Image (spheres, coloured by chain):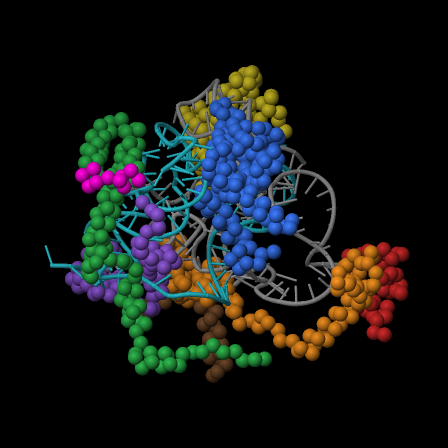
Chain colours: A orange, B red, C purple, D brown, E blue, F green, G yellow, H cyan
Amino acid sequence: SEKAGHQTSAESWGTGRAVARIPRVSGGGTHRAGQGAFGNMCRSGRMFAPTKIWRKWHVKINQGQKRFATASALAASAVAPLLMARGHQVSTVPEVPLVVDSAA
Amino acid sequence: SNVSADLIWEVSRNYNSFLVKQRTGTFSRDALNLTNQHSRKHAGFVND
Amino acid sequence: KTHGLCRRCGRRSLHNQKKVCASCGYPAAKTRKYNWSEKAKRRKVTGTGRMRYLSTVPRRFKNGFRTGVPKGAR
Amino acid sequence: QVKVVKATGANRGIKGRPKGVKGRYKMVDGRMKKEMRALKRLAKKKR
Amino acid sequence: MKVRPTVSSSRRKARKAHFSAPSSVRRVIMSAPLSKELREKYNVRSIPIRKGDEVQIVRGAHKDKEGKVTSVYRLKYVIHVERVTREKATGQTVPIGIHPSNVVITKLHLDKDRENILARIKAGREQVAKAKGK
Amino acid sequence: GKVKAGQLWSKNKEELTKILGELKTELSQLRIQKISSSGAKLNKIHDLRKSIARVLTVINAKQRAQLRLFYKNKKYLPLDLRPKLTRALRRRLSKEDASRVLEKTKKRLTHFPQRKYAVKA
Amino acid sequence: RYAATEIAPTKSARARGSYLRVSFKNTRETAQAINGWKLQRALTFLQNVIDKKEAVPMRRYAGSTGRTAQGKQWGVSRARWPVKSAQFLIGLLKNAEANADAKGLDTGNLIIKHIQVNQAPK
RNA sequence: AAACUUUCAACAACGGAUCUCUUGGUUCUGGCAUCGAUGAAGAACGCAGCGAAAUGCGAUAAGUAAUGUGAAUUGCAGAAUUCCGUGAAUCAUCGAAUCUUUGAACG
RNA sequence: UGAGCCCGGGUCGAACGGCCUCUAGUGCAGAUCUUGGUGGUAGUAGCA
RNA sequence: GAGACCGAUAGCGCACAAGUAGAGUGAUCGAAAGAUGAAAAGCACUUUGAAAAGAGGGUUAAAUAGCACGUGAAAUUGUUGA
Ligand SMILES: [Zn+2]
């Protein structure tokens, strides 16, 4: 959420105080008062580089290369040792480019 | 032809369903391996 | 004390001299609201209360706001 | 005029003005000491 | 595999519905199977359990124990079978909760509504069986 | 001490009111003698109050049905008897006014209405 | 569970108390004072500490402790009178004596084989 | 030698880390468009056999009518249901009702 | 060599791992770091 | 309806009687806090104790799970051993 870690009102106490120069929640009658916030190292604060929906989730691949890879995959499926290497129990079936009858 | 035992070895030298790789050596689960070591010499499925 | 009980919102926020609520502004017909306080907007937005009638509206919309009784009743 | 308060003892980690009744006060620390030494070094380099 | 978009395959929603379902949905869930004689008598597999049924506990620590249902407690999805009880510290007998999935119905409490339920289930089963057969 | 809603639906005004009067008197007496040894008498009083609610509901329903039949062919209705819907739906143009169309548009639609046609492959 | 698990439960009597609102340091000092003693001697000593006749030597937690001649009983200079911890320990020793009587042991020859004080939630 | 200080071990403490879980959150996608003087959103006071909060309801007050299912609710006490029934339920649906003081709030 | 990896014993109860690729909120002693827990001071100052 | 997302210091401030407790005259600020067990079967009874509680005995596969409850690290502490 874009508001995760921003839904607080904190301000640095100052420079001359013997406390870390970090934003701290105002108030005075709750555990949250005076605690650090707005930081990636602070509990219940923001995360560094918040994840956003624009990440390039999809990859554009040339159609020529897609077809090349599909052809190579078909040739590999024709090759017999590659089936065993990929992990198919192919020992009781003959004719690796296996064809069944269309009428069947 | 486009397929040769060299091609199968080069395609399958890094990863196989038969390949067992540990810190002390790399073995082979292939039933056509006389030594159970990963090598071009003993790759039963690779060699013709 | 400068803040008494406001009848519209129920908070101890009625300046006795100004007679204006600091939270909702009771004398004004409109309820006080500012876009710079999303937290206050979400504290006093709809859904934080009882929902006496707006909770019953959707069922009537689903059934089409029909009037009458089922055939063969009583 | 402006008084200096060292943030130790009862004055360590205080939100606002300490008990010292004065018109203007300034809190000090070792981090500020190092910052001031860096600023003086920069000024001396400039001059 | 799920095809219709109305159906949800989500664990969160499934468990929420199961543990927040009202009493009628709980009855449907606490449906229990019938014995074999009743299966070939009524062409019915399972029916919702009720108070007046005689059942056979066939799963759990109670291996093969028969008894009449005393009370169905829909809140924690249990039923109470007669004489299936344990002594507390004081020695007072308290019922043990058994699941309808773990019991099997041997004698069914007969009333007009349940006869209608059986008739509808049997009619659907026989219609589909005839459709599959011919 | 439970009245049946269906039973109360076949009764005249005096009948409903006499039983209701008896019912309130019974409630008062049972409360007075319940304040000591409030038990199954509390259960009876709860059922008695539910009976009071049932009788009131049936009387109100009968009176409203009579009022509706009285106003069946009258142009103005009481606001209580008028349908609720929503404010926007109540202020929306009625179906006849919304469907009303100009005479020229009606003539054009009468003499040149959208025809059915197909285009061959 | 008890820390000393090497003692058979059929030959010994065990006493326990938890969340006791008494000072941990004073209780540790008096428990160490009465460690390894006979039951009668320990009870007499604790009653004397109540009556300000004998003093518990403070060994570990004894910062700025007043001096008293009774300390010569222990070869130490800092001794105190932890009255409330003494009462708590008297209660626990009485519970242990009652347990020994229930089990049938001879109360005239019991020794404090194990005693332990731990910290409780603050 | 003991005490005290320190180191290692066993056991026992304080503490809630690790692993596992999740009726919660977050993001995306799809169908639909419905608050209010016929008194809204919000605030208040009450209502349960035994209730403080949460929930529901409004002097018909953890609710009524009606419709469907068809034998419960539950922590305890008390009543049920005849089961061959217009009929239990802290049930679902929902087209009729009740709806105290205010609040745009209107003698 | 090392970062680390594997085994034995005790506890524990419900999921987990190796290998080839992919992916990232992926590796801490510091930041007068954040949160939480706990120490010495200390049974001390002190309780007018 | 879903996800190469997060998994109780994370994910919305809120997985819990959370915009609650609480603070401020007020505008406003605003938390902490999940996990017994399959089933409470949540320890009958005896004894000590003023009580709190302890010791026997008991339920359970397990109380090395006792509603200070899954597992139970470190800091820090007690006892015993060297
Ligand atoms: Zn106001």
Q: Residue at x 52, y 40 (%)?
A: E118
Q: Quadrant of the N terminus of chain E?
A: bottom right
Q: Is residue F14 magenta?
A: yes
Residue B32: image location, x then y, percent:
87, 57
Please report the bounds of the magenta region as a residue range. F6-15
Question: From this viewpoint, is residue F87 visible?
Answer: yes
Q: Quadrant of residue C65?
A: bottom left
Q: Is residue H34 above or below residue H18?
A: below
Q: Is residue C22 magenta?
A: no
Residue A91: image location, x then y, percent:
83, 57
Q: Residue at x 20, y 33 (%)?
A: F22
Q: Residue at x 54, y 22 (%)?
A: G38
User: Relative to residue A58, is residue F44 drawn left or right?
Assistant: left
Question: From this viewpoint, is residue D23 visible?
Answer: no
User: Relative to residue F3, is residue F32 drawn left or right?
Assistant: left
User: Relative to residue A97, is residue H98 drawn left or right?
Assistant: left
Q: Is residue F68 above or below residue E50?
A: below
